[PDB]
Amino acid sequence: LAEALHVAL
Ligand SMILES: [Co+2]
Image (cartoon, rainbow, N blue to C red; front, side, top):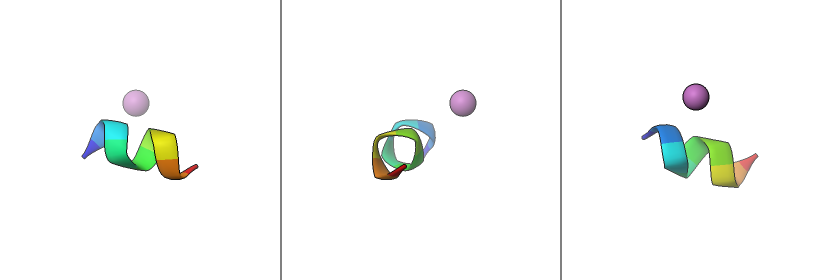
């Protein structure tokens, strides 16, 4: 979750 959102952003 954390990576997914950090890379989306
Ligand atoms: Co974080």
